Length: 153
Ligand code: HEM
Ligand SMILES: [Zn+2]
Ligand SMILES: [Zn+2]
Image 1 (cartoon, protein in one colour):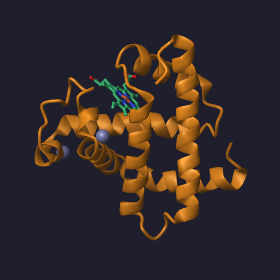
Image 2 (cartoon, protein in one colour; image 1 turned 30 degrees about the horizontal axis):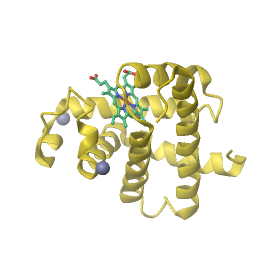
Image 3 (cartoon, protein in one colour; image 1 turned 90 degrees about the vertical axis):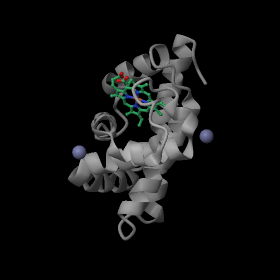
């Protein structure tokens, strides 16, 4: 798991995200969809977006990026004790949206990339390592719930 020093790194970086939730959210979803256009196919809501310029122009996509980062932030702030927050998310993503764990890996890479792009000075390799560990813990706990419900992978 994460050391206290590592949680400190994660939580101090997150405060920088909270200074511009919509901007980070929009950048992360666009990075995901450009890097892995197969992920776009899971969203009936967005699958009509064919080009990067169309994604940037979508107010609805920006709104969902706020939804995603708000939910992720609430989880990170629980410092590993996130069972009540994580369970409804695992439920809906396994049983309704049908999102494979690999796509959670892809969005984790997108988050790291955008944090680096927006915060090149402050987001050094130690914070990157710590953020990677936090996102791994998130995936590990979701995967456990997926396995319980008989989805896993
Ligand atoms: C950081 C990881 C993620 C977080 C925190 C997250 C959070 C959420 C939240 C809070 C909702 C709305 C409530 C719900 O339906 O559960 C949602 C909806 C959804 N999510 Fe996720 N999500 C994440 C990753 C993904 C990925 C990687 C995909 C697909 C590749 C995905 C697909 C969806 C879809 C299809 C919906 C329904 C959207 C709609 O039609 O309104 N999510 N997400
Ligand atoms: Zn891909
Ligand atoms: Zn706008």
